[PDB]
Length: 130
Image (cartoon, rainbow, N blue to C red; front, top):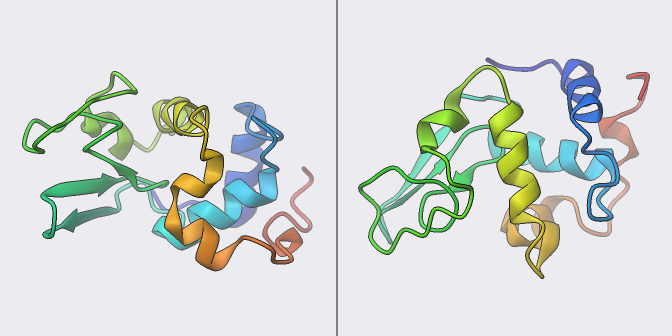
């Protein structure tokens, strides 16, 4: 499923993402925008290290979810990577919350540093009623 901007904003707020571990809703939106374009089916294979990024937040298979074909997999979210490709983003959100519980927080995603950090991210939630 490809979410409409405000539809996703309201969904994430209901799932308790606003202010989770100090991260504003606009930051989560900025992350989803640049990682997958709000697409739950997005998948990116990293030929360099044999890992794959899954879903709307592009969660990696080496540390977070299990896909069975990634060497040195940890599976910290205790989820099959298949769960991160559903239209229902509940599992993806639960795993994203786990990612930010680590020291790096939202900085765990390089795209956030490049496209969201120190920027005016209000545009991502403007007019959504959140």
